Length: 301
Length: 302
Ligand SMILES: C[C@@H](NC(=O)c1cc(-c2ccccc2)nn1C)c1ccc(C(=O)NS(C)(=O)=O)cc1
Ligand SMILES: C[C@@H](NC(=O)c1cc(-c2ccccc2)nn1C)c1ccc(C(=O)NS(C)(=O)=O)cc1
Image 1 (tube, rainbow over the protein chains, first blue to last red):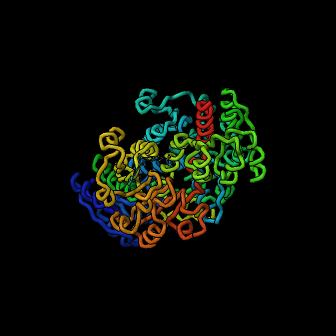
Image 2 (image 1 turned 90 degrees about the horizontal axis):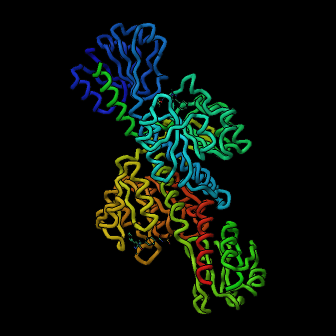
Image 3 (image 1 turned 135 degrees about the vertical axis):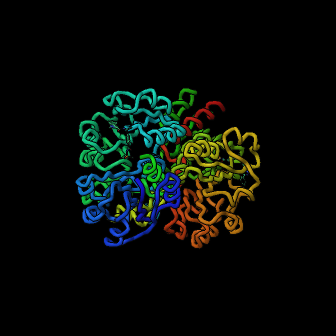
């Protein structure tokens, strides 16, 4: 409402937009509990990235605190329970990470078709394995996009330039909206048998937990390739492993895991699995857009 | 032309089209010099991939041989001098590989921007090194395309969808024609300092041998990423290694080498290098199209 503390490595645009909105702001970085508490004493708002841990002790000591803003998608460094007990609103910036998440997804799709990460490891091992890494063309193949928000939409328009047929489903996004970006919506039951590739771009909710499971993998065309650059849990990990074992799934690209880092290494260790350590939001550009978005949100209220 | 030997593993569509054209087809693979020569005794045509070596001794022993077709790009496995000397026509199928080559190139670009082969290796080694990785967003970045034939054009239209600024140069393709597919042509010297990424799609010629060398690498902006899915030697390997070691080049993706497989391991072993064993044409679709294209050429000859 009046004063905000930026307590992490943020792009200068964040301070600029807050001040333009009529808010006073203090910019500091890597503070200790007491240092953080002292600065927060006359602040209604708090802006963090990944370094600052917003624990119960910090929350309870900041009596004027009303909003905790995280410049990014995930809110693991913030005690959600302590904030909710105190009536503090916890905000994130999902839009800022959209482009980098969509780009990584497209890169993963290209990696599943041509096994570039596996071919690199092979080359680095002094091997020259041509027959093994015989791949597939993307042109003319069907891409099923489950979740048609900003990320799903950006993935669709990029893969359409490769001549992929983009189909999908989203219960929030209308068929008219998805048709404007060339995505034909079909009932979920009808999507599984048509896809050569399937990508998920939904939030993690009870309705989206295990969207790809033993039953849906069995409805897929044999040799389907799957991408999960959204959130760990949307693809049932045990069902994905069984599908890769039988060959029902020809390959998977995972940027997210139900447990991070995953203690069960069976998926990561599978030869047909490509993975990243949650790098979807890991670009200087996404970080700047999240810094900008959080300042825009704070001004709006 | 009456009998054709297919001496490498080809798509069944090749044999099927040749037979539709009235030709007798024999399909064999992994034949030795002696075995290949014996099969060709009653053959007017020979279809190869890259494993069959059409040497001077093979050409000279195959007295009925009229045509040698390669289901793919180039003819490095065919003795072009011996074929020209004995009046033997040599055919290939470069158009059959274009989409697959352009798709691999785009995959290489995305792999360099987000260090995907490195992240996979780190994960497979049982590590969670998120803090050690920082990628680059392609949107608004400049991609320089040297050579604007079929492959260069296909790379451009796909990377345009990522919001990349596509500039380039080709002495044969007019700036008006490249503008129609969104590639802004500028004098070669103006291209180097503008690119975040450079990809080569030219034939290997005296003018293109070492197109990227110590002189042109110095002209590039610090941290440039380079892709070579065209021909080994267009990017000077020695100059690329020095640029990688200095940081002038932030990363390189190589499908092709001056020597295949490469005995010099300096580039392949570099942490910022991603590579493939010449996989540009390695798709079920590209192999099927090349087999189809060479069969149509043989049937057109009869
Ligand atoms: C547009 C909206 N769609 C949905 O919410 C949605 C989609 C599905 C669904 C279920 C089954 C099959 C296919 C789709 N179910 N639901 C509840 C959406 C919202 C946020 C993100 C997002 O990416 N969030 S983020 C940046 O925080 O990860 C993405 C999309
Ligand atoms: C369009 C044409 N361009 C040229 O020939 C050309 C380009 C350059 C050049 C030199 C310096 C800097 C930038 C470009 N110089 N020249 C003579 C071309 C023809 C075939 C391929 C091909 O790839 N063929 S293939 C599938 O059989 O390998 C590719 C392109």
